[PDB]
Image (cartoon, rainbow, N blue to C red; front, top):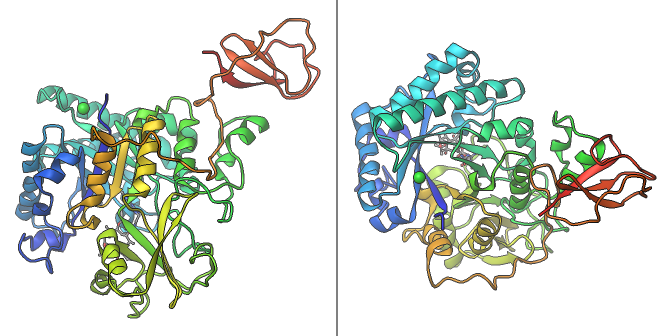
Amino acid sequence: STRKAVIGYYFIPTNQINNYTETDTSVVPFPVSNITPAKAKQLTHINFSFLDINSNLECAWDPATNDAKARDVVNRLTALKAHNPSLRIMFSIGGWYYSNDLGVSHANYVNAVKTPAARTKFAQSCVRIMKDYGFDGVDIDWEYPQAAEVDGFIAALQEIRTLLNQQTIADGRQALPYQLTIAGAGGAFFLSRYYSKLAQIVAPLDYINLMTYDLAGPWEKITNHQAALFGDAAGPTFYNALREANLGWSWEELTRAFPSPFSLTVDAAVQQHLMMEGVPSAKIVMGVPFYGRAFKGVSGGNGGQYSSHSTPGEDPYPNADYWLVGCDECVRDKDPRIASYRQLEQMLQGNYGYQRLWNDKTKTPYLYHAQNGLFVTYDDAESFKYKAKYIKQQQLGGVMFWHLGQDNRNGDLLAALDRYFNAADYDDSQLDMGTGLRYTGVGPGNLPIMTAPAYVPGTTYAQGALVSYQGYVWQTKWGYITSAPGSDSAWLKVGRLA
Ligand SMILES: C#CCO[C@@H]1[C@@H](C)[C@H](OC(=O)NCCNC(=N)NC(=O)NC)[C@@H](C)C(=O)O[C@H](CC)[C@@](C)(O)[C@@H]2OC(C)(C)O[C@H]([C@@H]2C)[C@H](C)C[C@@]1(C)O
Ligand SMILES: [Cl-]
């Protein structure tokens, strides 16, 4: 029954706020008025982005922001709620630019969560901003707290939660209670910063919106799909950093949960969350990108997949060679490395030399430009069928995407997601999910259902024997074992009784 969340980022830069207008797309390419009533019904959340944490360690707009124009923009978004009583306008604190390890505001994030009093002041500023501008909830997109910061971050979220709950009571908003989300890591290297404390991070949240995209990029040496649903054995694999997380698990426990190397996929990130105890599937939201990543200097043979390449990683783009043929938005933005889905349709449709190819293991499309040696990894309405099917099958909370301004003009990507979850006449019972590589890790949070003969005292069990005892199915790690399962280190808990 429960409606899947559909969570769309709305991003607008400070200069566009300060010059806001709905009638000149050279000033504001994606005004609020582009979010029509029909789009509004298809969304459950819009994440307005981005606010920041200032040096006073409070949530704040960019100080260069014209406040009356900011209100007017936010008012336009909340007016959308008139077409859809389920819809929320969240706001988002952070983003890569403000909050990455080398970001301009980074130290503010670290300091805002550092002490009890700092957290109280920060938490209060969050709810005060929410109430003053008319937002429906708080999203945190710190990319990413690390190590020593994680306990502070967790405490900050717990405190925001309580303050949100007070506010919900004060405004009688039990029908649409104020909510708390974060944008979570969607790959294991960044996820490993807070993985051991994942249950604590998720507990105060309504959702954790996994950034299961940007899993490939110019910083990797080999081209790859940025959001492969499942793995391709011909593609690159990666060290599983999670096996070095401070978990206190045994060798066998670590090995069964964290195969290494592994395929960096959407399914991997999702399963890595489900493996942890106290992380419920309904709180897990799959991120998807409404943009492609482009690579140049690729050699042929497999459509530009898994190729070396010559794409600069530096920021800003180091020159004016805008080599993404047909991408007009790339010229406007002076960077050929990322193109909106909206632009990609146009590139494919014009005579620009791209073929649209399909990897049936990853269930994702890609563009290949054979003449110039270009490769583009992106998602479309077809890749979203498989992802939506996976969302229903794994009982996830829904879908998130970055970002709304990158859909095509008729918003076909958002309409597709809405249809795959909610349309009466859409049927995916026969959609084939393929033979791509699944992440097979098992941990305490996702033990499969199993049967086996009851454990018998006095019996000598060989290596690999399976018994049932006190709620679970257990496996001997070596032989010959006669101890009761769970009473020493010889037995591995591998499954649970119906
Ligand atoms: C959370 C995020 C991603 O931030 C984007 C920026 C940071 C954008 O990052 C992405 O779009 N990344 C895709 C993955 N998404 C995320 N990391 N996070 C995310 O989805 N959060 C929900 C990168 C590719 C970018 O365009 O950076 C340019 C220079 C390369 C940068 C940093 O100058 C910049 O340039 C513009 C295009 C003018 O945007 C601004 C920012 C100054 C804004 C502030 C950043 C933004 C929104 O474009
Ligand atoms: Cl609700």
